[PDB]
Amino acid sequence: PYTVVYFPVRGRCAALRMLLADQGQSWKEEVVTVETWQEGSLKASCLYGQLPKFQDGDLTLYQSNTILRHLGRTLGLYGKDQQEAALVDMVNDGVEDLRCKYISLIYTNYEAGKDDYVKALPGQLKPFETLLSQNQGGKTFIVGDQIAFADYNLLDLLLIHEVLAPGCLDAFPLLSAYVGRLSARPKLKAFLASPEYVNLPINGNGKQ
Amino acid sequence: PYTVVYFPVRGRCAALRMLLADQGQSWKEEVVTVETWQEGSLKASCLYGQLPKFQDGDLTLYQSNTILRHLGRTLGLYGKDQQEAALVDMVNDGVEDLRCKYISLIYTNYEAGKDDYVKALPGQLKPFETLLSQNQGGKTFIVGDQIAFADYNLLDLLLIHEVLAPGCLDAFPLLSAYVGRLSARPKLKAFLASPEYVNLPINGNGKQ
Image (cartoon, rainbow over all chains, first blue to last red):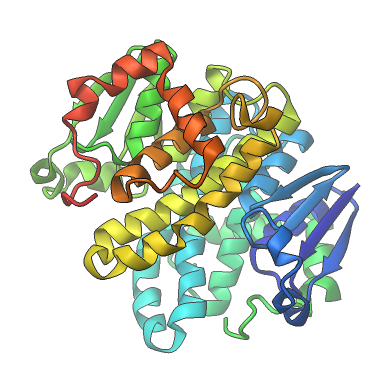
């Protein structure tokens, strides 16, 4: 069925794993260690020299968002129509932008840039709160009334920021409620509480 | 029909403009001067505080790749099936990653970083030459045998790099031929030679 090749961390694979668990899909995890990665042969076979690598039958994919979109399309988590699909993409692109900023902080200048990043955070989260408010008063999902691949990506992004800055969602009632509601989904709640998820570090340098 | 709100530059709108021109679609251009932008009303109303803003009927969209994907979906430029669509996304994500590096250089450290960037460039282009070689020997498009939104994005990325580093494609026979072939498409060729395209600067700071 599905195969996820990645380092022993949550990182860019956390959202796709949540998506697979919540949809009741089965998959295999191929763990790649820092030592194996420095060996160089695997890396040189990765299209863009980076993990994760994903397999669906004999379809080999790279790029976390490409994988999320693929699963969204094949599992019916890409909106009810073309209009919603476009909005789902818009949300995911926004999520991706902040994730890049987050990743940069963690691996580039964590000690001297965390305060500045946390201060600017509220401004970075407001867009999602607004999107929520424009869709049924934020009582359902980010787009429409069915879950999309973007919801898992957004959920992950929010969860890791709560770790980086506890209480960062206190000012956002819709995002806070949204996190609680999706975290309660039966299959997702089970997964989020399992060793598989919990005992994996968020990032590879031990910072969070 | 379509409306594109953007600064008087090619930047992130060049690819979608080429796509609209090549597909024979009409669209209006709403030019936003830096003056008008440094004012505030407009920017504050953009979902993520950035342009371009795009309208299809009453559907308002932000994020260049969201727009490309929307047009790809509604105009049939997203692959023949689900497998091709996935590959198309993979190509576009790669294009986006390099564009981010390019944008960074132009706007962050053009003077002291151009040599280093040009030296690493070959390694950044090889992946596309590789995908091209695996599809009918690079005799058609990047994915399958029909053009996709990714092709226009890739085309733009290659064209701007030729400006940044003349001859950078000399080492890539498939990419070079690919650029010539797509540049020769009737509607696209006409568009690429028009004042509307030619008299607009590539970036906003006058560097390229």
